[PDB]
Length: 50
Length: 50
Image 1 (tube, one colour):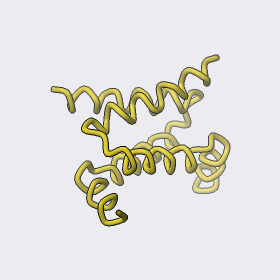
Image 2 (cartoon, helix red, strand yellow):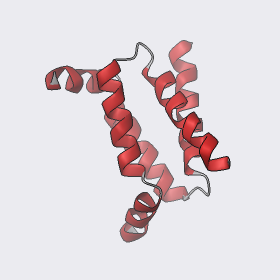
Image 3 (cartoon, chains in turn cyan, purple):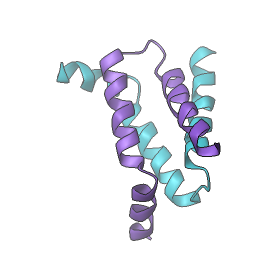
Image 4 (tube, helix red, strand yellow):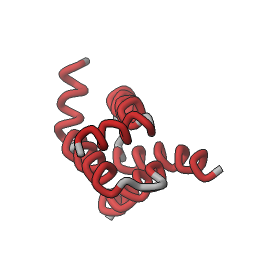
């Protein structure tokens, strides 16, 4: 079950994407962090459905 | 600068929200993880602008 999760996270690059989203949040300091995160992933959702 | 980031992350509950998003991803195993994350934060963006 844990190994399952580990593999899924690895497969979809979740660790790096979340890492990067946190770095951009702290760097930019959004007035609207939730909007920022939504838009961050929305651009990735776009490639996913491409 | 690091303390700055630490405080911002703490202020906006970023650690717990990302933690929870990862737990739901591994639990549900989305065919579309990026869509999942976009929608996850979109619901939070909604409360943010409320």
